[PDB]
Length: 244
Length: 244
Image (cartoon, rainbow over the protein chains, first blue to last red):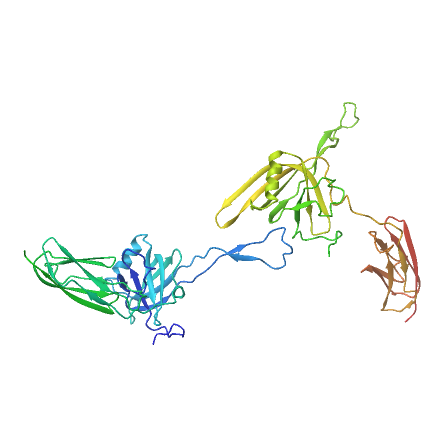
């Protein structure tokens, strides 16, 4: 249904903030580590500007028409307003973002399956109080550097497939096992994943660079879950830890 | 069309340096043995100046005022800033010209069909570096000897080429006749004139558009004298005005 080659109605646009380490420009589609800014009243995204540079010389033949070229770009100052919920986790993060000069990344997800990623710092934090109307928080972000517009990405293989091949065998104290994940839906992939531990008593899971290691801290039988990105696909494995 | 007798807008002025072995002042118009200095950001021609000489004596009758005469003339220094292109010929030649200290000739070609040619040595080589702005090499050349201005190779024509043909008719009240003047001794002339009546009562005169206009305010025979320049040439017109 989402067609990036056809106009969209604009309803359903969503705002996220990247509260983590790594490259937000790498995999903007995966909502892992992105915190949602819910209840957005309205949003005016930033404008990609460009300054003018004079390229005229005295020796130039004739000067009847001006000659100019592109200069610096300086794309920034995107603003929005959302319902004021001070006690909600995600707005306190916004206030902390304002209270220091941190230049964080934020993304806008459009109903046609496209994402625009910007990086900037909060330059205006305000409010509007009036009766018979929800109190609104107004925010403005000055962007720095080059954004990653939706027109930079054009392939999106959509994946649609993943499985798990675990050891599913015994585990000894002080010895850790490794489980594998197949994320090759016909080769090309554009999605990451994560894994968890059910109890954090019998076993612990370390995830990095597709390497997933289960260590049997305590004996017993535990289940290791895996969730791919936003949660489109999941998997469950079983690991047994022996006392001897 | 270039016109030395009318002001020009200065855009398109070019700078050249002599790489030949002949006489630079011989034929400045031809660009045969000349190298262009392209991408000239701006130019400042050298200013001619002559110091003062005290021409007073003890036995000079009156002293309440100072008596001075023209002293030794100097051609000043011409300073031009042009875009920095170190890999192109013309800037390497300029650097060598500054480096080995010889007195070379250069010329400025205005958008007039004229040219001002100087001789001098480079007394300054500079550079300006700043982001968002082109790197500019700044050069100052101290001029020596006598410069050859564009006024040196101008030509004046005084071949006695004034002819005056009047209306030679009967003009009426409320209507004005015209009188034509030819100033083409082979087509070229730089001398003007002045035309007026003899009594300013029978007819009122007005010169404009290289033409004479006579208004027949009063009937009778009126005389219109015309004198060219400093009284070398003249003409007399007779105009008859009728009652109607």
